[PDB]
Image (cartoon, rainbow, N blue to C red):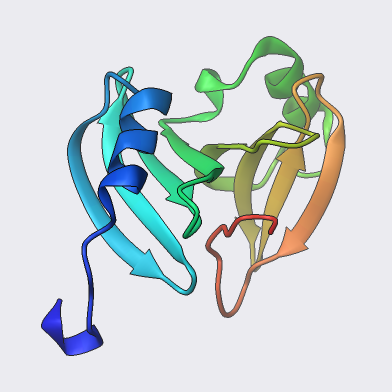
Length: 141
């Protein structure tokens, strides 16, 4: 909005989204720091698609409904983990232009809140405490 001096994205950024995600609909844009973020629906899922000022794609976050939307190796890894008993608060996919190019993030709580980052093959890449402050996901660069 006018209150934060929002400027709409350049046509190049908009075109970059259309190329990456031709099926994207319900597109709304926002500025965050040095990024533009498209909140949209694509391929049946809610997504947030991040671009830099050069109209280069840096990350997509996709909302998943539950652990049952995780691929087999990832669901298995979660259910084998020390956190298998914890309450699940959210499940998302993070995709990036560099490796590891896909992370599945399961947010669990048992007093403390923890984001569990899994590789596609079911390996635990990160356990990040998100009990306080920013529990949101930003690009790597």
